[PDB]
Length: 578
Ligand SMILES: O=C(O)CCC[C@@H]1c2ccccc2C[C@H]1NC(=O)c1cc2cc(F)ccc2[nH]1
Image (tube, rainbow, N blue to C red; front, side, top):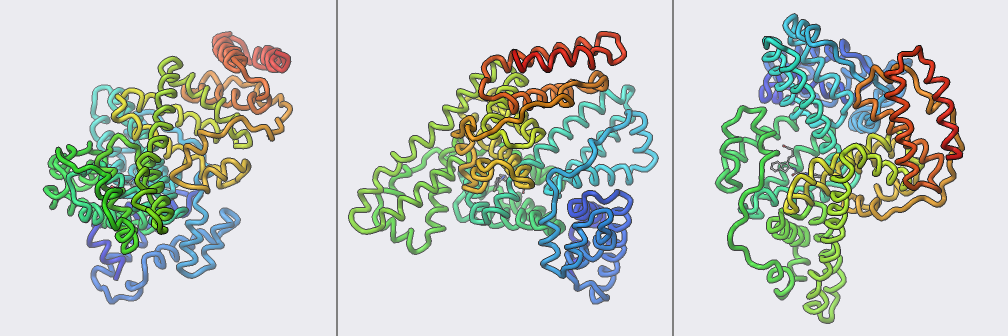
């Protein structure tokens, strides 16, 4: 019995929560009350299997049980329609079909949060429903959220209201925390979407490689064999979470933590404090810990991987173990190399070996391999330096605008809201990484960008328009960023001539946050460039100034939406000439 094993292992509290997220990530448009009804029926059921594992149904697989139960509300197409398709299939077709239809951009409201007192009224009135709501809203919006982490944040959500709803000034306590969790939440989600894309679109060999490089950069003292064991374990975990198998993911992550802490001495020295933490924190902590000291003595790379003889012999006998060793050795020495750089280097090594082992002087042709790595190292460093140069002169907001312009010219077929969300997350690199010194700049940035471009890749894949986006995304996971970097203004592109409705704003603009107000200005920008790229000097950064003033002047004009219709029409036309 599976539903039993996982109840015993996770306990009722987590068990209940994971199931909520499973259902919410599979049926996003479906309402809260329904998912809560469903989860409860499964929990009622799981307990019976704990009492008696030979009971009827207990030997069904979790998808079987979870799927049957979802479909008791999903088959109704008049509401969903397409989800009735998976419901027609048996497993494993149906679970494949549910994954197939996870919406990265679901037509869901923006979640408004009421005032602190209302909120705190809801929390003490019934904190169990309040929390269930939190899990519900995030997962349905983030169908690939790493479920074990969603539990760790729910704890932080709960603890905030617990504390802050007794503070003398509740808001000042609460709002910083909620926002930090909103922000920290978004970022986990993106990180986790790149993991699932690796696995689902490129295969586990990719995930391993990324994992091998990554884990090794953190645990350079550890033997390859050990890392391999951590990787195989990490792989299984995220493979499970990416296939919808959330109980088993959560559980396996918990075992991985337990193991990591039992064997600190074989893994790292930065762990001691994480392993004293509570169970939920214990794993998150581990994932966000600084690198261990690099072993004082290490031999040169070249010996084992160039200057040795019978390099092909090892390559032949076990290439995946030979290339993994390279990747391990190279990564543990180079914690300033982004993980994707390490993966291109590792690929450039594989391709060369294929060429050289044919026959003639190998020990010669593959001598200058390390020479072949030099350009790959600098190419991205240049861009970070350069794009950090531009950051401090422009500030975070103006820099985004520049990236918008850059990326909107780059790939102008792309949906506007996409361009904006993306360009802004791209812009966020400056603040995060430029802060640092070069030693930690490259991995910070280039990897952070990897997350943001995979973001673009998925939101695009949904409804593909530009062939250049589809190319850079499908071509090669590791090479996505150089691929976008190298693109240039699209000559093919026929502009859309104009529109009236798009630029004359309404009064509600004044009542929105600077956050959302910048977003309304940044949309405006993106449309203009769509309408007029051919010419695109400062005149872009010029006519932006023309809208921002028009926004704030009419939001302090004291007039009944007058200038928005009258003075808003004078401007929009003027730039078509100007
Ligand atoms: O399972 C988790 O706790 C989240 C993953 C966190 C991972 C962890 C865990 C312990 C020690 C170091 C580290 C590094 C940390 N991330 C990765 O290893 C990692 C794998 C991976 C695979 C991809 F296709 C793309 C990005 C990736 N990052």
